[PDB]
Image (cartoon, rainbow over all chains, first blue to last red; front, side, top):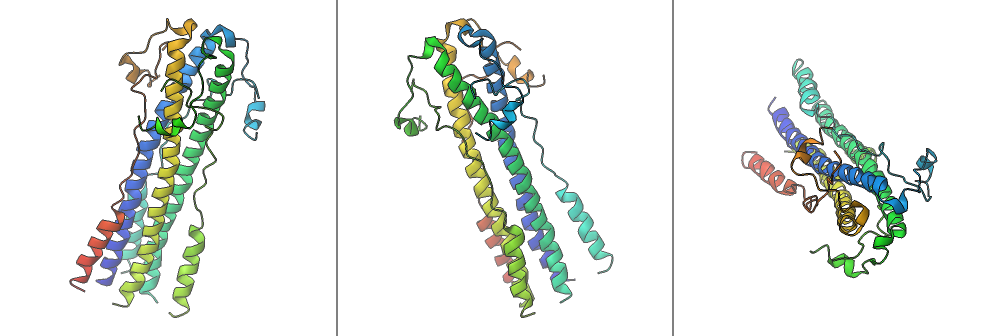
Length: 105
Length: 105
Length: 105
C-alpha cells in the first residue's frame, strides 16, 4: 500500500493540472463570450438604425451553408453565444474510482 | 503485473479527463469562431455600404504593430479566424507507449 | 525503484498532454482575442462617425446587469479583452514534487 500512495500522488498532481487548466480556459472563454455577445448586441442596434443598410436583409437558414464558403446579415438575434460550462465532476468520479480500488486493497 | 494495472487505471482516468477537456474546449472555441467570423462578415458589409465611413481606409501591415498600442479599419477580409482543431492522437501514442511497456513486462 | 520508473513514464505522458493542450488552447484563444479586440476597435470608430447613431449613448454600469437579460452601447473602450496567459509552472512543481519523492526513495 506504500507504492500505491506514490502512484496516487503522481495521479493527483496531474488531476490538479487538469482541474486548473479547465478553470482558466473557461474563465478565458466566458470573458470572450461576454465581448462577442455585446458586439452582437450593438451590431444589431446599428442594423436597426443606420438607414443606408436597412435595405439589406438577414440570411435565412441558407446561412448555415454559407459557412462552407453571401450579401445578407449572418448575425441575428439568435447569434448569441450560450454560457460555456465544462464538466467539473473530476473531483467526484476520481474519488469514486479509487474508493473502489481500496475496498479490495 | 498486478500493481501495473492499478497504475494504468489511474493513468487512464486522467487521460480521459484530458480527452474530454480538449473536446469541450474545442467545441466552445469553434462556436466562438463562428460568431466572430460572422460579425466580421457583417461588419465588412457595413463598411462597404455606410457612406459616412466609406472615406476611412483599412490599415496596411502597420496594423500588426497597432496591437502593441490608429484611425483605420483593423478588420479586413483577412481577419477571419481559421477552424481550430487540437491534436487528438492522445488515444494513439498512449497505446504505443504502453505496448512498448508490455513487450518487456 | 524499477516500478516507480514506469509510474513516472505514465505520469509524464499525461503531463505532456496537459502541457500541449494548454499551449494549443491558449494559441487558439489569443487568436480569438485579437479578432474580438479589432472588431471592438472598428465598431467604436463607426460609433463615432455614423451620424444616424451618434444620438445613442453608451450604457453606464447598469451594463453589468443587462447581461442578466437595453438600447445603448454595451461595447466601449473598456470592452477590450486582456491577453490571456495560463499558468505554465507545470514543468516546475512537477520537478519539485518528485525530487522530494527521491530524497527518501
